[PDB]
Amino acid sequence: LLSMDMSGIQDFIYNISGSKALKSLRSRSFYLELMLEVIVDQLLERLELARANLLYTGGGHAYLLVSNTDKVKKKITQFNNELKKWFMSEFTTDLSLSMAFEKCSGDDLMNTSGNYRTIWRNVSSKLSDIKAHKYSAEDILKLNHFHSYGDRECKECLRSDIDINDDGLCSICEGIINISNDLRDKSFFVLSETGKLKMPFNKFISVIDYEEAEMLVQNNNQVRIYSKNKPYIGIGISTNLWMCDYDYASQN
RNA sequence: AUUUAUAUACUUCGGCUACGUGUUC
Ligand SMILES: Nc1ncnc2c1ncn2[C@@H]1O[C@H](COP(=O)(O)OP(=O)(O)OP(=O)(O)O)[C@@H](O)[C@H]1O
Image 1 (cartoon, rainbow, N blue to C red):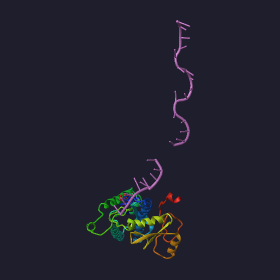
Image 2: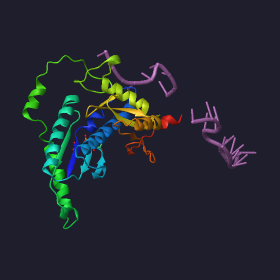
Image 3: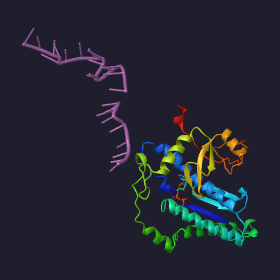
Image 4: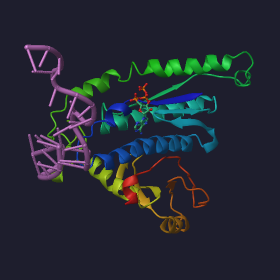
């Protein structure tokens, strides 16, 4: 039973002070949500496994029931290592993820003597105490010695480490603005290798409509269409992602 | 030269901080 926790959502989502703030917030919550979705899907691809194995997602949590094999464990550990590398490379304190798992048996799941709750609490506890130790030695040394030439804080996004560009905006928040602009009109989001917004596994997210999504399907491209609460799509890798995106300002 | 001594009605009714504008280089 594998559990994942996102570290810093309540902080990173609430460093917004600009005039376009509302557009980013819809884009920022969606950005974290899509991060979690793409990372969990990518994990399930590593496990050569099915989507039905995801028991619960939401907030910064995720719950999976995967095979108890040494192979599974080595893959989980390796992907955790690469994952931690990537987040350290992009935000380094604002967002982190945690991995944890604890053995369970069939007798446990069948609700024999309430041990289901015992294992649930055990996995929660291991997830919540592995967050104490997040950084090995060499990583913490690696952070502290970068006399690296960089620019200053993003206006929309409060971050010293980030480097601003045109109009005093960094790349990440400008892409956030663009995808926010596209949010209200277009309903489908694609996982593509060129795209707009930087995403974990060397991937990028852009926006599509059902027709060019269809062409992408007949383009046999390794794509995952992520939708805005649309059933009956039947387009490639159908992913009716569950999200509430409402704005009265678009009713004018 | 011998009785009043101000009396009742109404004791303010009608009509209820706008703009430049919030954030950064
Ligand atoms: N994409 C998101 N955008 C905005 N708020 C979110 C998003 N995802 C989750 N949240 C909410 O923000 C809350 C605060 O997140 P927080 O940073 O405290 O991390 P967490 O997931 O609760 O875990 P922990 O605090 O143990 O690290 C979450 O509990 C959740 O309800």
